[PDB]
Image 1 (cartoon, helix red, strand yellow):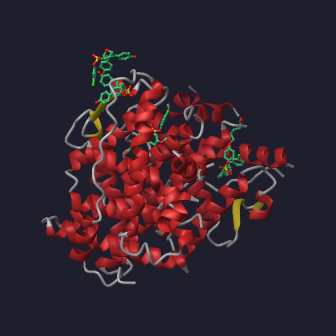
Image 2 (image 1 turned 90 degrees about the vertical axis):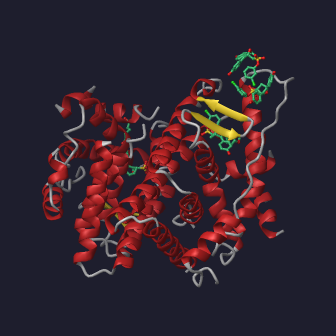
Image 3 (image 1 turned 60 degrees about the horizontal axis):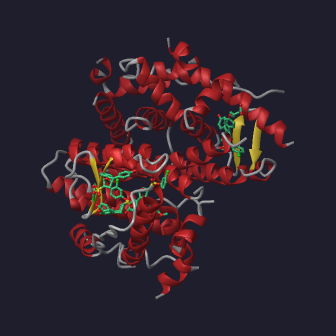
Amino acid sequence: KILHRLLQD
Amino acid sequence: KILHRLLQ
Amino acid sequence: SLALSLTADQMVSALLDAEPPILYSEYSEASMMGLLTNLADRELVHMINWAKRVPGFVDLTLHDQVHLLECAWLEILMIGLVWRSMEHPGKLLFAPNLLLDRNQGKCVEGMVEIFDMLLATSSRFRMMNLQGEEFVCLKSIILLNSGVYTDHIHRVLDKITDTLIHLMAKAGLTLQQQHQRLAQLLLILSHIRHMSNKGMEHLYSMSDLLLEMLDAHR
Amino acid sequence: SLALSLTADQMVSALLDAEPPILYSEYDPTRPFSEASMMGLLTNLADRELVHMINWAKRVPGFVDLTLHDQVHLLECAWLEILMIGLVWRSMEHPGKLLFAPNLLLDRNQGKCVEGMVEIFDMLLATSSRFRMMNLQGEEFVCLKSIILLNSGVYTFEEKDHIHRVLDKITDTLIHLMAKAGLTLQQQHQRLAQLLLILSHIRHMSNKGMEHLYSMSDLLLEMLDAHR
Ligand SMILES: O=C(O)CCCCOc1ccc(C2=C(c3ccc(O)cc3)[C@@H]3C[C@@H](S(=O)(=O)Oc4cccc(Cl)c4)[C@H]2O3)cc1
């Protein structure tokens, strides 16, 4: 998920 | 409307 | 208008006196939708009488009264259902002879999701120890607030807020506990709005009075 | 969790510093005035705003204490609400117009260009008019926007208990702001109620907005996918 990745970076 | 008559 | 001149206790007693009765349902996915549709159809008649007795509502014009009810009717049905189900954890008391759990909600397609939201609202009301005097204040707020954006109404909303704080202060809550509890209750109304919108969208996807209440959202 | 240890002033200054910037829309004189170009303009705008929103949410006190699954859930439920209250806040000083961007100021007549959008335009305009009449302050706005982020997905998941305590802290912050502005105890509770009731309308506008969106940006497709 894009939202999942942006919250990790 | 039915709501018109019921509110009268 | 008369509503503004009321005291807190007179506002509370007027709302409690206007409470509609708890109706029974009639003694498959279609079998349940019929039971719910018939029950909601008879509750709407009692909702219109209740709305007439909410202080400040009759001061509105006939057109604005119709508008608020068309916007808020499913919200009002839902918070009533959630209030009735407070003492029955994990179950929704639609009627005293119709007590359902989330598994039975799966019988109708797409209803289990709204069931879980309703159950979560009831558990939230239960853990807050929501009182009857607070409940009728919240239900009146929904009626007056849900269609106001689509100044007398705002003066009545303030009076109900003062009534909510008066109830919390009389129960011994500190100033901080009063405004914290007020906020908690009002934020729940946003979820009740969310549940209504999702419920409406499914209703005009599948009674003579419902159809027109359902048609107002399409 | 340092969110509960923050004072009211510390909570306000933290929220003000986390504020995302005001973005500009594309200005393409080659594109014609049409439904597709208007929607493309709004889609491209909200798409870039979402990147800033995700970064803003990390700085909301208490948000990073949540698990990654719950952070994803809250943003999926609330992203359109947060875009809308931002739009409504930017449009306060422009009566009858919606400032989607400093170079994109639209009235309700131009909202008729997309089928069915004018009804939501009218709801956004009335909300913006309500904020202008109340004289909503920036410190109150940043509290309301953080409340939306934490509250809109809290009953659709222990983790709920932490969010509720942070929400109470933001309530204390709003009351602190109003008491600092000279309002009486009665006026404080009344204004607190007026602000929170508007959040019910913002939820309504988002749901009606989402419904038209998943009927007609890969990040937006996934955010739009969560409400269906
Ligand atoms: O075409 C026609 O003529 C008939 C249209 C009018 C029907 O009228 C209805 C039907 C159902 C309700 C319901 C409830 C209710 C709550 C409190 C109460 O006191 C009475 C009823 C609760 C909440 C809604 S729901 O959101 O779950 O909706 C759905 C339910 C199941 C599946 C789907 Cl898809 C949606 C539903 O259960 C309400 C009105």
